[PDB]
Amino acid sequence: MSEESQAFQRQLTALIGYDVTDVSNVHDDELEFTRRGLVTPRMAEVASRDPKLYAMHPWVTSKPLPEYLWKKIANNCIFIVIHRSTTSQTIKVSPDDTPGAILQSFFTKMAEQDFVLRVCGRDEYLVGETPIKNFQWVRHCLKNGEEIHVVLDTPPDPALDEVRKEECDRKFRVKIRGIDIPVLPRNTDLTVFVEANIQHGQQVLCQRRTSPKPFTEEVLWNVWLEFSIKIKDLPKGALLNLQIYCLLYYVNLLLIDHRFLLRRGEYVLHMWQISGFNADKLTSATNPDKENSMSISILLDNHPIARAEMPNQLRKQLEAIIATDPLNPLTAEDKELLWHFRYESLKHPKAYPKLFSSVKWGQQEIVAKTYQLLARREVWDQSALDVGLTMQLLDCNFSDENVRAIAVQKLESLEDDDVLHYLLQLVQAVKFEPYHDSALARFLLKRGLRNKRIGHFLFWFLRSEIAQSRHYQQRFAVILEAYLRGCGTAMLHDFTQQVQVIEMLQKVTLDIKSLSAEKYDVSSQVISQLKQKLENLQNSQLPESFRVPYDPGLKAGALAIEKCKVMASKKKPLWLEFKCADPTALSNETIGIIFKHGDDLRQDMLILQILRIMESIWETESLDLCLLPYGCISTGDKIGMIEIVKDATTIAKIQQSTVGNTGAFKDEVLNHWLKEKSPTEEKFQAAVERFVYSCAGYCVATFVLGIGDRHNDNIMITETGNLFHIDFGHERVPFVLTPDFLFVMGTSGKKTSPHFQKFQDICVKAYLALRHHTNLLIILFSMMLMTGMPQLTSKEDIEYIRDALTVGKNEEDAKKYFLDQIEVCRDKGWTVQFNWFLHLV
Ligand SMILES: CNC(=O)c1ccc2c(c1)OCCc1cc(C(=O)N(C)c3ccc(C(=O)N4CCN(C)CC4)cc3Cl)sc1-2
């Protein structure tokens, strides 16, 4: 291994934020085995991808143009403005024209074909055989009433993407020797025992306990725990879960390894301490902190794997069971039905999750029958892809490799555009895979390496987790490294720039947070030191440019130091502004970015991404709710970026600017603000309309997600009328619809009006459009809770969304339910809003 290659691994380590060659925290070779296992999938995708299309990463969709976007084209014509160093002719185009085609109606229309169309000021290309109406940038421009400005230039050199070459029928038992912790002192000395569980898909096959003993820094049982399950019956993917109760600590050990071998020998496992149900509890990783953590010693001394028509009424029971929601509990009666009627069940793709939860995974013969069942998979294979269904089979309830692979098989058919929609949840779903190398992980690897946009986000989503999750960083690092080894030198250089930038801003963030207290109010002293420090960075270890992490097509240049500052809030986040490093840009507007330290931005990414999913869901229904899921990215431990939405203010600041002593609240302020920021009544009417739509979308989305009761300071609005929520980091009301919002709607004092009627109509339409996707929403909600929050009750917390989506009810009762919800806010008026500030005194 050349000295060059060692320097390279060093490079990857700094981009990843973890050393994948570190062997300090392992008890076997799973991780190394996986690094090697992933080489094949990587080389295969690299060798398979088209260098040209890969370099230009066109962003496209096969989906039809929504009704609400056809509205803006009734002339069957679209205008593209091409530019080239001086003047710019505006070509009239047909929505079906191909980029190379409009290049024919150009060159000849003017009068060598080795040129390509690129969006002005962006690293975005319109290429490939695709109708221009199928390009996302084109649809984004129409939806925003913006013109499509493009520049004619030379295709990027694929050479820049060069990738560096690479080079027994006995019952199961376990001996618990004892436990050891360096320091126990809490308050009162209690007693302690060890609980050993054998689990599969968060289902206990057998449970055993040790006798209680005095809790001292060292407790030695030296006791055999014999389980009812036979060795031969252990399913691959089963975990020996070990727990200490006084519940204090846990740790897991895969009973059958990545080689299909039964675990054997001595183990000293360092455990995880509970913070006083979630994905972290399922991890096969052990606590890396060997100095301050509890450990448990165990011994293993115990390779494997070597007609009749249904009556009308049972079938009805069966179909009823299948119709129930993902969260409906399956009775013992229900499971037996599903299993007995196995072959009938297999004819309904929607039964798959319920059927595989009916499997007795602790019985070799049954599992086998199950694999036999999966053999004739025709009905499933030809079924239309249902993302909600697929994700159900990737959650914590399925530990079987084969069950999860068919889920992954269905994902193979997603277009890149959809992958981007679900990417974050798919990455989080890697936490439910029992092995490091899995079909799900390889699919993400493959898709990321196939498309630059997916690779970029895949990188940040992985790095965010590597940086702040001890439970999963090892697995995610191996995945990221594999990816980094195939993305190409260009991407590598880009990621390097981005990582350098955020690292510098982190330093700065910290140093500046130090030069001030815990809030007040800053301090011209504090702002000046910031500007100096940035001036220092600017010249230079701070790279010429870098891609915006939440908007990779955008290249950020030099900081505009005069415009930077520290925001006035408890935490002291930076308000940074940069110049665009692309001369071809259509404006002088800077790139605003908020850099913040002290908060875990992962919950916000999760919420913002779900918001994006709701928008695409609504698109599948021809609806546009005008949400504004601003860019947000966890870039490392307790740090990240947030997009600064231009021309936007807080609803509270608007209130506050007019008196606002102790937080008095006037109904007409909002309407006045909008009218004053409008240059004309036209623009004002557009603002009001957009407000109605945006208000409706956020009321619905926020109710469903159970995040509806918010303080005014957590909700913003653009000067153009777009309302939107922010800060999703962790009497009552379902959502925020205050009298001022109502005032803009032309209503006041519980009355009606054309815009308000229009609002209720949009809400209801929005609400029921989401109910057609109930299962997708429920499964995303529950995964989000398991992988993104603290230790959430696996029933009651998750059950909220079921109630919220009013599962089980017909359309009439649903509309009713929501309309009453709208009434509650009205009756409550300003109460909850009003309650703030006082709680603090
Ligand atoms: C011209 N644009 C803006 O002023 C602006 C302000 C805030 C945001 C923005 C634009 O983009 C939209 C997304 C966004 C998201 C935010 C967020 O998540 N949090 C937690 C947040 C809330 C308040 C502040 C804050 O201190 N201030 C200073 C007072 N000012 C009136 C509001 C923002 C900072 C953050 Cl990061 S702030 C914010």
Image (cartoon, grey):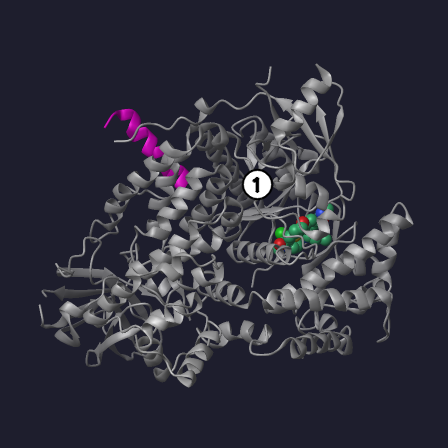
Residue drawn 76% across the image and 45% down it = 72
> Callout 1: few (<14), some (14-19), or many (20+) C-alpha neighbours within 10 Å?
many
Say left or right for 583 vs 548: right
Q: What secondary structure is marked by label 1? A: loop
Say left or right for 545 vs 733: left
Task: Indicate the position of residue 780 as horizontal and vertical percent values.
Answer: 50, 62
Residue 128 in view in this figure? yes
Which of the pair 718/452 is nearer the observer?
452
Residue drawn 27% across the image and 74% down it = 360
Task: Indicate the position of residue 141 as horizontal and vertical percent values.
Answer: 70, 41
Amino acid at pointer 1: Val
Q: Work out whether 384 lies above or below 117.
A: below
- Find the magenta span and give its range: 1-16
Residue 370 is inside the magenta segment = no
Q: Work out whether 284 lies above or below 513.
A: below
Residue 322, located in which quarter of the rendered image? bottom left
Task: Indicate the position of residue 19 as horizontal and vertical percent values.
Answer: 32, 42
Which of the pair 399/551 is nearer the observer?
399
Task: Indicate the position of residue 279 as horizontal and vertical percent values.
Answer: 39, 63
Which of the pair 10/52 is nearer the observer?
52
Say left or right for 658 vs 84: right
Name the residue that disc number 1 marks.
Answer: 60
